[PDB]
Length: 167
Ligand SMILES: Nc1nc2c(ncn2[C@@H]2O[C@H](COP(=O)(O)OP(=O)(O)O)[C@@H](O)[C@H]2O)c(=O)[nH]1
Ligand SMILES: [Mg+2]
Image 1 (cartoon, rainbow, N blue to C red):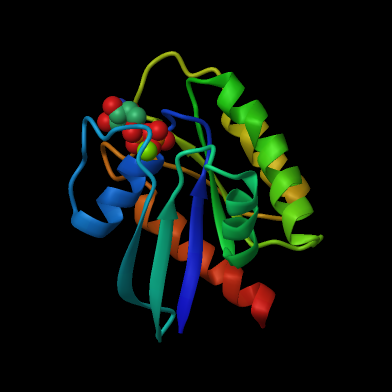
Image 2: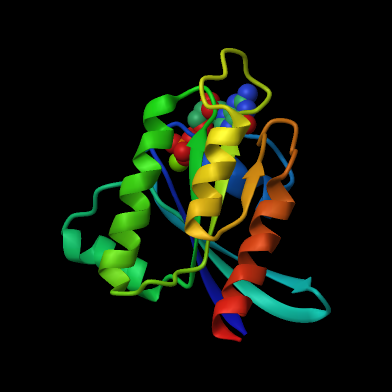
């Protein structure tokens, strides 16, 4: 089965770098922040094959209805912030609200991702992010697209969350 995964978060948090590690096994140092693209990858998770369709978002669309549409078709959401950027963490509150609002749903599969854990000047404590995820009933995973810490776990965990919702 094909699953639609959507990677959301503020500009610069590492959405593209996380996605390209999973898809292409390398860490990109410069990927235009304004490009939005999708990637397909066949995988096996918990013994069951599936086709991932991963949308690496980049923010505003020509029409806001198009952003609403990809949230409606999206089955699970990787909500990414950067651990050195408090505003990107605060934005998670808005992503949670907006995705639920567009889907008109109280139960939306999501994983909270705190990326850039290899960088200095952390401003978001592990506990603060874990507590937020727990308040939503979703997993929290610390990642680094540079070292590949957590990357594969984040995406595979999101598929598990999608299946738990559908099952
Ligand atoms: N050190 C480090 N750099 C990262 C990490 N993730 C992304 N970057 C870099 O941070 C910048 C923004 O990443 P990008 O994936 O383009 O962010 P996006 O705007 O969310 O798609 C780029 O220079 C990436 O190489 C990370 O986990 N660690
Ligand atoms: Mg990007």
